[PDB]
Image (cartoon, rainbow, N blue to C red):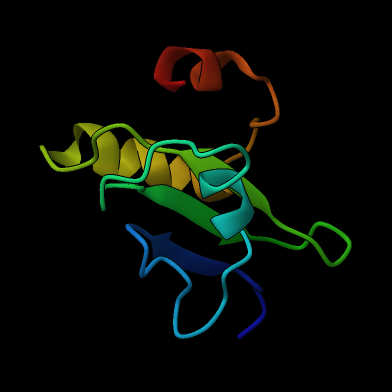
Length: 88
């Protein structure tokens, strides 16, 4: 009982976990991709009351992305833009 982290799996048009259509703007920022496959990982950490997003192209496979996403959500380094260049 100490660490404060919130991970969520936002996907398709039903991505607004319950009723949180935040990133929804990105899906409609200009008639972007909307083939019911809009998958985006959203993780909120102790960033002075804030969070970050992460576009995903394919997560269904194996641990190869399981651990890769876990770290991307709350790792030691991050904010490098390198790993993002490999995915995005």
